Amino acid sequence: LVPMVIEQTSRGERSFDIYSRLLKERVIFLTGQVEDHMANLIVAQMLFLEAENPEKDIYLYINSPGGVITAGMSIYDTMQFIKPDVSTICMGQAASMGAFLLTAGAKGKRFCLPNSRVMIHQPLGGYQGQATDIEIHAREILKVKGRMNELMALHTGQSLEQIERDTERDRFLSAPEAVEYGLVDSILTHRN
Amino acid sequence: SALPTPHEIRNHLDDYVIGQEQAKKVLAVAVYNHYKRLRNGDTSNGVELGKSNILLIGPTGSGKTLLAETLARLLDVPFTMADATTLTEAGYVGEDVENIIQKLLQKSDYDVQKAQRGIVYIDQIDKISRKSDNPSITRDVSGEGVQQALLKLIEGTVAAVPPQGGRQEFLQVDTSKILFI
Ligand SMILES: Nc1ncnc2c1ncn2[C@@H]1O[C@H](COP(=O)(O)OP(=O)(O)OP(O)(O)=S)[C@@H](O)[C@H]1O
Image (cartoon, rainbow over all chains, first blue to last red; front, side, top):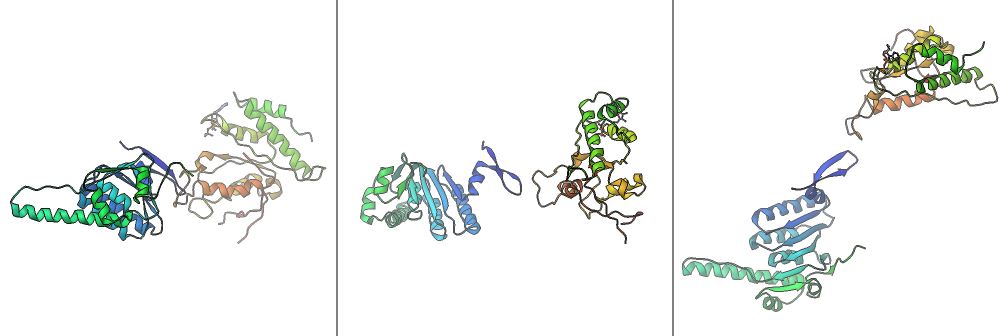
């Protein structure tokens, strides 16, 4: 169930859901696993906000354990394509793909909560069949791993060799370490 | 030429109304003070004599219409009775605000000097209340739009009245001294 709220406007009262109320203020929620359906919904929201206002910053809340890679890359290109600065915030956890969208935010407008945690690793996959087919899918997943490291270095500022060594296995980074790593800019401890 | 007292007029209404004590006191004091205000006409030491209208509220079939009618019998100045449910905002198909003054002159036989000293009553005022709850584009006419028109009437100003049933001759009639219930 989702609670309903009432917004007071000059024209009259309007009944909106808790998620639709925040969407009116340029706020997007990223919850659960990243799949084809949830990702296609966020793209429509970003495009809709772009037309409504191209000069106001967008707020993107990321709390997800990660998911499909191809579903996440569609959102990455959208964030870089549109003109507005997509502000990103880390709530709870940020896995491999959840962390990639976090650092992909606009430079200087990336924050992480004091108790959040970031995790990064290499792409996961698998295949069953003839040896000729395994080589095809093996070369493809290797290119993705190389592509994900190049972009990670671009936003984090680190070198490509450093990202490769750290992503060979799961690596957890607390909120303070993420700032030192260039993944985020600051922490929103209290309201000022 | 002694005028009636609040006690005398109250006993007159007791013979036609039952179970209403607080309402009788209001009409008696208001009608009593009315005669004094018009009689002086800013000629005594008291200059710029104000006005105080009355607002009756009660359930249906309580006797509001009875007090307005029974009071007119003992009242010397004329009296009328209209309804605001048919009123519109100066131009729509229903009615005009000046229709109230037209019915007032019929009782006074077209005597402007005597009609200004009369009394007026309105019925079914709840129908004039806001309809749209902080209105929208529809531009409510039966509601809010009627209240704003009455504002000047109750305070006092000149108006326009058809002489014998028109809708090129208009007579000016002040309303600052006229009471409204
Ligand atoms: N207090 C009363 N004493 C005697 N008769 C009364 C009394 N109240 C009402 N009546 C009778 O009820 C009739 C109608 O009274 P009304 O004044 O019309 O009631 P009402 O409260 O004004 O209803 P409205 O004005 O239409 S909302 C009168 O003509 C009387 O016959």
